Image (cartoon, rainbow over all chains, first blue to last red; front, side):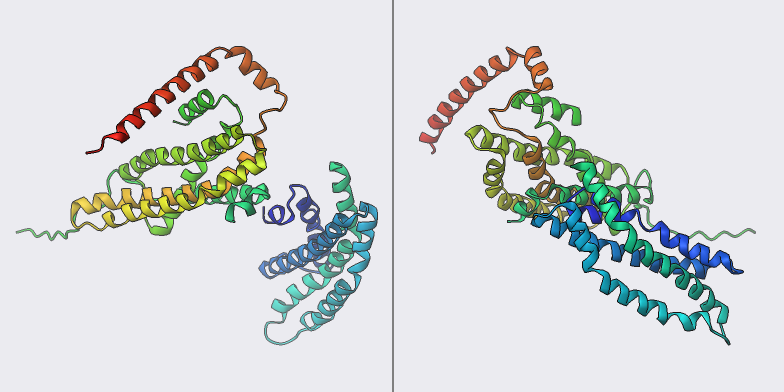
Length: 148
Length: 50
Length: 198
């Protein structure tokens, strides 16, 4: 509802909402690869993944719509929107990836409590950024071509 | 004008109305029911036997 | 009551579009009331339901006023967008004024002492919340729906309009003639009444 009200359309938020499961996939694969369990602290770490995926998708879609309104076709608008946003996503992905390594390698009091969330976030972040970079322009163009 | 904002964006009004409807539907099921409101003053009863 | 208002709107306005606006305004303005009661710590009883039944009339009145003004503006000869602009240009102020005066009427009579005030408080608070929510809904939903669904006087009729014309073709004309004659007589009567005032 909030996204549809913001975007003045009833189909655009579908592209943003159809991206969040991939971060959950990445986190669950990361936690399954090692000896782990889906405890409460693991469930805690998926909220940030979903929020960051939404943050990534929303602004790219906004820029694509802004360029579309100017008089360029969906192909060029999507290509330019994908091109113009590479640097901030690269910055935040690198910062958050390198900022959670001490959580994984923790010893002492409460080591496991930090370890579970650290492994979950660390193994979900790569999937989140990969799919956010390589999936949303196609979703946007497909949705745009559906209406015509 | 307040109405001119909503005239050109019917979807905003639709979202607001749907939010109000959802809030009402969620809240209606958590409300006490009685035939009459509390009008009888409270009282305390002490019982003894001899 | 919903069926009755839809029927009377169809009969008086002779357009199937205008019946949509009240149908989507009556329920919401009721349901949104319920939540606010949980904000004030109230419970439903006979008085609250009676208040709802009575405020349904005020909600219908407000919707009727807005729709009728927009339809009159359309019958003047303007397109839907400009007709809606002009109609809402002279209704928001009185809407806020009537909401405020209904609040000023209803709020203080919830402060009686004794049993009478205990019975009055729930009814007054429920009706005040209902009318406030109805005014808010009328300020937002109604003009947008009127501008979106309603069409011009020179547009090609659709299938539903064709059916309603072929079923009710002479009743509408007879009603229009009777209404015009009655309006002329009432105008003459009010002109006569105004002359003598002592």
